[PDB]
Image (cartoon, rainbow, N blue to C red; front, side, top):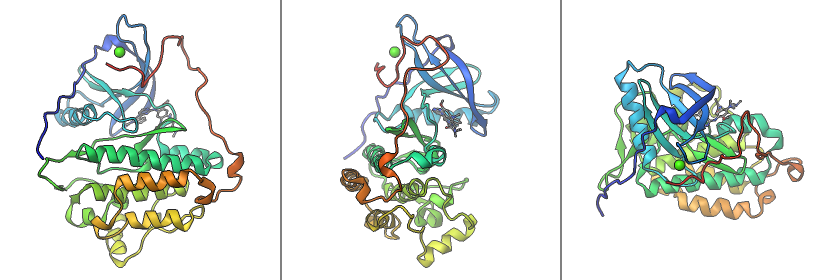
Length: 316
Ligand SMILES: CCC(=O)Nc1cc(Nc2nccc(-c3cn(C)c4ccccc34)n2)c(OC)cc1N(C)CCN(C)C
Ligand SMILES: [Ca+2]
């Protein structure tokens, strides 16, 4: 069919309504703070991440963050990052749901001794659900990676970073890029060679992300530099089977790395397979002391008065 009106609402927030509390990170993206958003007179406090950029002076900083805002305002799914609004101060700030446990790559690196097979398989299920939703929305992410998955709780993760995301027209079936830095080691071969991006190249990146999780955050092709990756992949070489993975799981990864993009799994099928595996996790991932491992959860604690606060439960 054809092209439906995007009737998403973009909400403009007054800077009055949110209190920054701590800086979380800074660098190329700008500076991300954690804070509280209090819509006036509604008796709620919503933990948020506020992304400023370095300078009000660069018009393509503003253009890039506004494109990110367009994309994020157009998605609504429990496993995709939740955009709350933008504030049009001198520095244009993007306000999203605070994800207290950080990015998933560093989370697995930091907690590898406490991560059982249940958590890993559930994360794969949830990531596949988010990506299948994005495919439903005809959105190609183009930067799926463990660093670009955020952790609301150990039981709940969401896909983030839509800085390279592209929405396809209904008649479009692929996006053709024109230069610009791209993460080679997560990229499908046809993306590396012809700058072609599809939902199936996103499937390739999903495979690499799963490899990251199953190795507890190892760097893919650790030694190799990016220029060699193309011919490495052309020779037929792929990432190795992680120690904890049965052949059942590794075969799924390998299918994600097929050269024929149409022979790769579709995201709905990855949902199905990984949930089947999640129903008997120790049969598909072999982790020592798996049975005794447990992970944290919130117990109502931060630096403030917080009787009036919550997060995903603030609709409209
Ligand atoms: C820097 C890695 C990281 O994720 N840090 C982190 C993030 C959040 N929260 C959160 N929520 C939504 C968005 C973001 C976010 C989005 N962008 C684009 C960002 C860029 C830089 C930093 C954060 C964000 N961050 C957090 O919440 C309390 C705590 C932490 N840490 C201090 C734990 C870090 N760990 C490795 C030791
Ligand atoms: Ca509200």
